[PDB]
Amino acid sequence: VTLFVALYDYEARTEDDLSFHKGEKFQILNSSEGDWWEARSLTTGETGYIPSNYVAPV
Image (cartoon, rainbow, N blue to C red; front, side, top):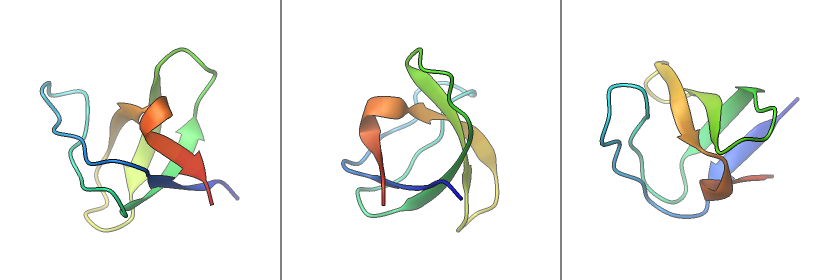
């Protein structure tokens, strides 16, 4: 299991990143370090690339 939370709000500025507010949950499926992890929004269901530094393990 890999449930992470957004420590801060983020405004997706591209069609590859996602947008949410601090307190949202995300399912990291492919991190591999780097800078942009792929998390799936459990609220909307759409998956995208959110800032790895903007999420943390619950």
